[PDB]
Length: 110
Image (cartoon, rainbow, N blue to C red; front, top):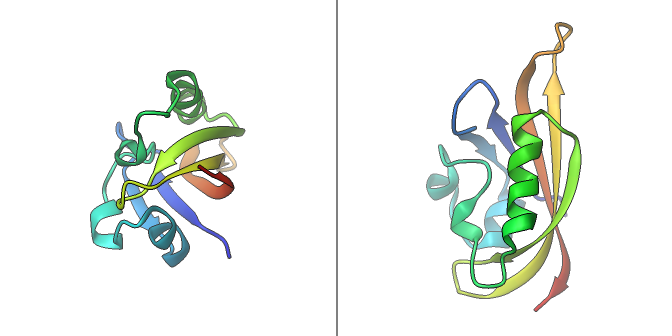
């Protein structure tokens, strides 16, 4: 079903502090590999990955922007797939961004 990850906004690299079973199976990477890595998931980038699609995801994380970005991702098996990234910032009462919730979903296989 769902495939998501939680990032630590209070860090420079927005290190992934959690990734559910769904994400790992989707990208083909294990939880131990994903943990502590930049939530932008650069390890999923490849040939078709658009620089604009990536920059948009980066910007969202920077300005705590709620944004959906369609980006071409590559699994560990080299396979490529069209993924829709859902950058969901999570703020507190003070409006400070505590953590990030990124939701991935396959748009099309290619």
